[PDB]
Image: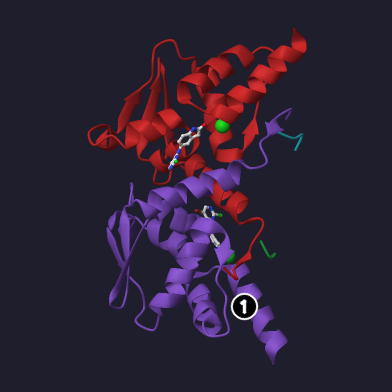
Chain colours: A red, B green, C purple, D cyan
């Protein structure tokens, strides 16, 4: 086509979706990770995670307001990944890398799994 | 704005 | 912070939200523009438009499944802008620029209004 | 991935 493109549009959209998340505006699901609860937008979760895409396209699970993750999932690792979904920024640290990688594999977040594998390989 |  | 950032994340999120729109997955509102209807995600509309942000943060309108735009709004101009919201690409043409600019002013989409004003100024 |  003969379209023009606004370079910052995608980043500005995500920044606004994160602002809605911070103010708990139009969040439509609670993700339960053991004793912790995380409110989010189903559409953002699906856009970032192969697991959430599969969950919310299911004819029964699409209507659930609460999703319980596997008990092996670490709430801090989930929190780091939820923040990454809404910001593009990943708080990857020596102390959390194993939990973040395990959570990203479970959530099917391929690019996160890739950088975790590379950061681990560098320290061995 | 750019030509994509 | 000491975060790392994935450059393409925001673009990939928006691409996936557009895929959900194309398959009519988790759309939660119909925007009525005269005889035409447009299905969308309230969160994406709010993230792109000052008017939709104001509408869906209203304690009564947040719960509406149908929103009727002013009868002066052109359905083609709205369609072009809805596509821009989900893609960052704007199909701006000599034949549609007046309708697109009028629709972007109504929707409160400041960057679109700005490029329309500049393209009009160049042709005068 | 980059240093933002
Ligand atoms: O690593 C990742 C990230 C991700 C996101 C989605 N999400 C969607 N995929 C498609 Cl094709 N259409 C709409 C949506 Br929402 C699917 C798989 C994966 N794997
Ligand atoms: O030209 C534009 C585009 C736009 C988008 C929003 N959307 C939001 N703004 C804020 Cl501050 N927080 C969350 C959301 Br969603 C507000 C105003 C405008 N004007
Ligand atoms: Cl990822
Ligand atoms: Cl805009």
- Extreme-top residue of the structure: A124
The residue located at (24%, 37%) in the rendering is A59
- The picture quadrant for ligand 3 comes to top right
A15 with respect to C81 (left or right): right
- Extreme-left residue of the structure: A60
Chain to which the residue tagged by mark 1 belongs: C
> Against C84, is A37 above or below?
above
| Element type where label 1 sits in the image | helix
> Against A28, is A3 above or below?
below
- Give residue C17's position: percent from left, percent from top: 45, 48
> On the image, which quarter does residue C65 sit in?
bottom left
- Give residue A34's position: percent from left, percent from top: 40, 15
Residue A93 is at least partly visible in this image: no
The residue located at (40%, 31%) in the rendering is A52
- Give residue C105's position: percent from left, percent from top: 53, 76
- Residue tagged by mark 1? C116
Specify the quadrant that holds the N terminus of chain A.
bottom right
- Give residue A93's position: percent from left, percent from top: 69, 18
Say if disc 1 is inside 8 Å of ligand 4. Answer: no
> On the image, which quarter does residue C73 sit in?
bottom left
Residue C27 is at least partly visible in this image: yes
Residue placed most toward the observer, C95 or C105: C95
> Against A2, is A7 above or below?
above
Specify the quadrant that holds the C terminus of chain A.
top right
C16 with respect to A42 (left or right): right
> Against A88, is C85 above or below?
below
The residue located at (73%, 30%) in the rendering is C1
Q: How many marks?
A: 1
């Amino acid at each position: 086509d003969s379209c023009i493109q606004f370079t910052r549009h995608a980043s500005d959209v995500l920044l606004n979706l994160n602002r809605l998340r911070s103010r708990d505006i139009l969040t439509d699901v609670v993700i339960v990770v053991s004793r912790e609860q995380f409110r989010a937008h189903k559409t953002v979760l699906m856009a970032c995670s192969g697991l959430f895409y599969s969950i919310f396209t299911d004819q029964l699970k699409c209507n659930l307001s609460v999703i319980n993750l596997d008990p092996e999932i670490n709430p801090e690792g989930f929190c780091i990944l939820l923040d990454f979904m809404y910001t593009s920024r990943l708080n990857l640290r020596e102390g959390n890398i194993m939990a973040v990688m395990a959570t990203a594999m479970y959530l099917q977040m391929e690019h996160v799994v890739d950088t975790c594998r590379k950061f681990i390989k560098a320290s061995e | 704005w750019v030509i994509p």
